Amino acid sequence: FQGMTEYKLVVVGAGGVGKSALTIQLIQNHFVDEYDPTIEDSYRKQVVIDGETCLLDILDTAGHEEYSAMRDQYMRTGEGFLCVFAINNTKSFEDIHHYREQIKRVKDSEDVPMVLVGNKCDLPSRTVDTKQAQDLARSYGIPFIETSAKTRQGVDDAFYTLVREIRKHKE
Ligand SMILES: Nc1nc2c(ncn2[C@@H]2O[C@H](COP(=O)(O)OP(=O)(O)NP(=O)(O)O)[C@@H](O)[C@H]2O)c(=O)[nH]1
Ligand SMILES: [Mg+2]
């Protein structure tokens, strides 16, 4: 034993869905109201999950990005992925298929640890129903979690659930 177990997590999804707001809530317990588009940013946090001390390396990605050899190179470092859409943006939900295919391509595998995240659950303008998201997640064999980066609903659960999926795959 040389130190804690390390887990490399990557947050993906369409522009504006709340990838950065979810990550900053986890790290800083702060809600970011401004929309500052991301290119690529990295964060770290030590936490305890199921009685195991873990070091989380979190990579926050761009939601507006053409094909990039450089995008593939950082995505291939990930061990697990949060696939994020916004519950008031039907196009972001339809884009989940594209993110899943991109991940399978870069990892060259059919069985990659992933969690489906439906964010902005605090807003009144829901267009994607809970049952539709749950059916999509069941079709992939992965968990679904509803979140709000503003209220903090589900934020810790999303990241911890992804770590649990990585552990099941390793073992
Ligand atoms: N009401 C509410 N607003 C949110 C929520 N999560 C994010 N937002 C808002 O949505 C906007 C975009 O959030 P942001 O985290 O920057 O999205 P992103 O997915 O990182 N965008 P990009 O891909 O361009 O980096 C911000 O104005 C933010 O305050 C939420 O759960 N509820
Ligand atoms: Mg961002």
Image: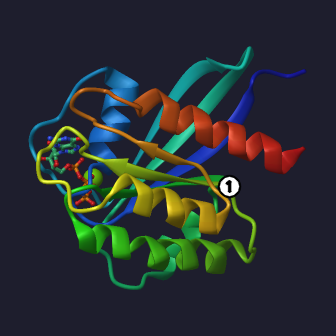
Furthest-bottom residue in this view: 67
| Residue 74 visible in image | no
Q: Quadrant of residue 2?
A: top right
Quadrant, the C terminus:
top right
Q: Is residue 127 left or right of residue 147?
A: left
| Residue 157 visible in image | yes
Residue at the (42%, 63%) spot, across then down: 132
* Residue 168, position as x, y percentages in the image: 81, 44
* Residue 138, position as x, y percentages in the image: 61, 61
Give the structural element (helix, strand or loop) at label 1: loop
Q: Is residue 166 left or right of residue 38?
A: right
Q: Is mark 1 within 8 Å of ligand 1?
A: no
**Amino acid at pointer 1:** Pro
Q: Quadrant of residue 47?
A: top right
In the rendered image of this protein, does residue 29 appear above or below residue 87?
above
In the picture of the structure, the residue carrying the numbered disc 1 is: 113
Residue at the (68%, 61%) spot, across then down: 141
In the rendered image of this protein, does residue 103 appear above or below residue 26?
below
Quadrant, the N terminus:
top right
- Residue nearest the observer in this picture, 140 or 51: 140
- Residue nearest the observer in this picture, 64 or 129: 129
In the rendered image of this protein, does residue 78 appear above or below residue 20?
below
Within-10-Å neighbours for mark 1: few <14, some 14–19, many 20+: many
* Residue 122, position as x, y percentages in the image: 19, 38
Residue at the (37%, 75%) spot, across then down: 95
